[PDB]
Image: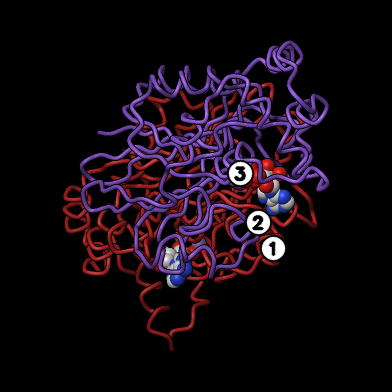
Chain colours: A purple, B red
Amino acid sequence: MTKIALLSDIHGNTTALEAVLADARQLGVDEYWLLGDILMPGTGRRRILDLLDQLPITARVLGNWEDSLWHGVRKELDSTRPSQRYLLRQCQYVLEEISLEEIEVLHNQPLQIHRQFGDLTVGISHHLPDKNWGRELIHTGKQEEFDRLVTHPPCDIAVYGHIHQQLLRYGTGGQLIVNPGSIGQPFFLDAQLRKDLRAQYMILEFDDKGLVDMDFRRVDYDVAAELQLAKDLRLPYFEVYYESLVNGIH
Amino acid sequence: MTKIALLSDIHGNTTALEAVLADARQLGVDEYWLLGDILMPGTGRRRILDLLDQLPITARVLGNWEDSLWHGVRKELDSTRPSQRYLLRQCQYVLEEISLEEIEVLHNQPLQIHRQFGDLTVGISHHLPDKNWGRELIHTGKQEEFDRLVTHPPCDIAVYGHIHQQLLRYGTGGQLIVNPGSIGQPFFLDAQLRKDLRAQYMILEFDDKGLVDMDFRRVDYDVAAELQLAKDLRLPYFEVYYESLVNGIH
Ligand SMILES: Nc1ncnc2c1ncn2[C@@H]1O[C@H](COP(=O)(O)O)[C@@H](O)[C@H]1O
Ligand SMILES: Nc1ncnc2c1ncn2[C@@H]1O[C@H](COP(=O)(O)O)[C@@H](O)[C@H]1O
Ligand SMILES: [Fe+3]
Ligand SMILES: [Fe+3]
Ligand SMILES: [Mn+2]
Ligand SMILES: [Mn+2]
């Protein structure tokens, strides 16, 4: 048996990540897959990289926020655009602790990879195989777009992140498509589900017979402590971070 | 915490049910929801109703195969169709151990029910809220149809069965939609996934903060023993049953 924790869309949420990593340790997870969006707009910098360095990471792919950080530290952002001004300040926050060499490692990652478990081929990407940004694979996405995860090249099970929602659905040909949701910025369109903003992740378990378990988990973490950490570290756009962690509005 | 086991699409598969029930009991499950398609075309008759009698079943909805059984024993099936002569023979088999009065109880079940857990309303149905048969909610079903599970009347989380596939997706408004899959007749369109025909069910765990876990489980059972039982009982259409359990073709 191999027990795999899918970690995605941490977004610098130090407290959520630590709680998810402790939950996974308790469950006796054997390996970790990192789907990307590691840093920003949350508190975590050095502490996030150190926690991941302690992990048996057997699969890793590039999120769009790794590209955004890369552009930011290379002075390609224009603050006259509100969205870039926001990103730039986040990059500046990150640059207080994280070097350019470490950012280079964060950026030097494949868009898509594959792993094999007996008869089963698993595809892994942040979003689309060739495109780690966009809205193609949202909850109401076209079947055509979802089929891209599992064909050309084929797999039996695709795992992705990016949409910040937990998911188990299918390619046209019956291939599994799974999403662990977001560790640091869980996303709900439903206002009742939104009252619960615990960290999201998932466990896959493979054994000699095939895929034996898909566990979509929620992990409690100390929100008040994360926000106190944001204040103390002078995290930019406190009120935006606050609203996403407390009210789940983005 | 309340830990709920969703049991769907048993289809008379005695050995698969016994295995799922032992897995559930080991997990400390607090209650069981029965999504329908209890009997036929598998082996279990009295044994299935006995096993379900020993459980804390807090929710139960009508499956289309319950309707079929009721119409079958009342000679209301269409003899001009091959599929319905197959069905009639399954009904006659069931009738050997099960009384007309029990079939009436099986048939007198609601199509859809609702349960509340704190802030969350859970909708429960075999297929569609007002239609327990057809192909509307297959893996590639139209979003308009899925939205019927979660609106008019509204709920935050709909659970259904009928398609014999595990599912976690969303209504247009972000409402959860889940499917435990089939205990007795797991259905795969993907050949590699089809190599593993373990029983499917799922666990929902609710706590003080909301839905904390969605665990989509596979349960190993002794297929050889179930097929030997089918022979010993003179189950009709042994070769169809064999195909369904060994090769996964329906
Ligand atoms: N269906 C959707 N409608 C609107 N926004 C969405 C949807 N799905 C995901 N998002 C947003 O996209 C964000 C994740 O993208 P990223 O910027 O790559 O972290 C989520 O946190 C949401 O705010
Ligand atoms: N996407 C699909 N394409 C073809 N057949 C399906 C699909 N989804 C479910 N089914 C069939 O419908 C059956 C369940 O319906 P029921 O007759 O109510 O047990 C499954 O055993 C499958 O054989
Ligand atoms: Fe993200
Ligand atoms: Fe069924
Ligand atoms: Mn992303
Ligand atoms: Mn059915």
Q: Which amino acid does label 2 sit on?
A: Leu
**Which of the 4 quarters of the picture holds residue A152?**
bottom left
Disc 3 crowd, CA 10 A, few/some/many (<14, 14-19, 20+) = some
- The nearer-to-camera label among 3 and 2 is 3
Q: Name the residue under label 2.
A: B111
- Element type at mark 2: loop
Q: What residue type is labelled 1?
A: Asp
- The nearer-to-camera label among 1 and 3 is 3
- Are dots 3 and 2 on a single chain? no
Give yes or no for contact between labels 3 and 2 (Cβ–Cβ under 8 Å): no
Disc 2 crowd, CA 10 A, few/some/many (<14, 14-19, 20+) = many
Chain to which the residue tagged by mark 2 belongs:
B
Q: Which residue lies furthest to the front in this view?
A: A75
Q: Report the side of B88 relative to B176 (left or right).
A: left
Q: Name the residue under label 3.
A: A71
Q: Mark 1 points at which residue?
A: B130
Chain to which the residue tagged by mark 3 belongs:
A
The residue located at (37%, 56%) in the rendering is B186
Q: Report the side of B31 relative to A238 (left or right).
A: left
Disc 1 crowd, CA 10 A, few/some/many (<14, 14-19, 20+) = few
Q: How far apart are marks 1 and 3 (CA)?
A: 53 Å
> Where does the image place residue A232, in percent across and percent down from the top left?
73, 10
Q: Which amino acid does label 3 sit on?
A: His
Which of A104 and B156 lies nearest the eye of the viewer? A104
The residue located at (33%, 41%) in the rendering is A212
Q: Which of marks 2 and 1 is nearer the N terminus?
A: 2
Which of A125 and B150 lies nearest the eye of the viewer? A125
Residue A192 position (above or below residue B66): above
Residue B206 position (above or below residue A225): below
